Image (cartoon, rainbow over all chains, first blue to last red; front, top):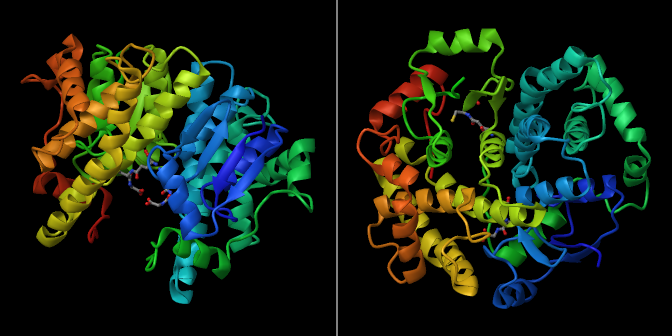
Length: 226
Length: 226
Ligand SMILES: N[C@@H](CCC(=O)N[C@@H](CS)C(=O)NCC(=O)O)C(=O)O
Ligand SMILES: N[C@@H](CCC(=O)N[C@@H](CS)C(=O)NCC(=O)O)C(=O)O
């Protein structure tokens, strides 16, 4: 049966999972949490090991913990390298883009003033720390992909991160020619091109409606700081 | 050559790595960051992909990102299950204890008042969310170990987490009989017993000296909130 993604109708921590499944050409279904009662019913069913989402029903498992879910999908669909060392490189690269996109998780919950500050913080991290690191990886081996000269989860996570940064600062990739070429190549891969196309399950930049729903369902995150 | 752990002379994010290596019976060396100049020299050498530590020199790699390092060690020393699904369970369990211990990372940098609040926050999470979840895993299959009826990284991460919670609230495991038995069994495993014994490389609860050193080296974390 198709994987079922339990989360809010928005990006959050589930977006990277949507990306990986789409990139692997895997059709999935989604169950959106829209009300407090719906969440309480979930808690009572005990299907959320730690009372939290993301949660993905896949291959008989009720998998929680974002990274555990991604690790599983990457491995199942051969996007995790060919051995222990390649997986280590993929994990190291993913850790970097996970931190980068992680700095944007609170963004929609921030005040107008903090959004400006956070945006500057994220762009600075991208241009001074992360983009230089990945540009160097590509420059050092000169291959089209980050690891093993073939598409991996690391490439998919980086493309998503690059797009999120560009949504905040359109010219953020300026000065990183290899990443620019990388962006075009990965975006053209059939499964990925389809995901970036209209009508896909890719979610938009989070808005006030998303925040309102998260707060209504979880009764939390009422005062987020940068 | 033996793995080399680059970090501060204290727990932080490197402690779990020390635990896993010790549990696997692997002898390692440590390089402690004590001065700003030492850190600047590291940055200039480019050995830290994202300008941060933990960093572990192992099998020819300059591995950064805590989870990437742990994933590698767990896999290399057969403490990651026997297949994709067992790894998924291990990752899900580890995610929970990583979050739990993660809530304690800022603790030594907190004010006296915030430490009291944070301690209450952590204990509540342990008794209402995490301990119940792991107690249930053990209860459901009745085996001595969390996954595959053999020692895994998940068991090691949970034991460490249990001990950290008990350091904050000694009777926190009360009401969780299976976890109590689990604590005694895992603590008795030769490699682990040795790590818990005097003279090991296990690090103590972080103190003001640790905080002072982190702030001196990184010139950051000057005002941490709960
Ligand atoms: N470490 C978990 C964290 C999950 C998490 O923080 N989930 C939030 C929603 S984005 C949640 O369920 N919050 C409710 C709560 O913690 O009580 C992961 O990576 O999946
Ligand atoms: N996601 C990274 C985070 C590493 C991290 O936050 N490292 C801190 C020390 S505990 C650091 O190097 N901070 C300096 C900085 O970020 O500039 C990991 O899990 O290893």
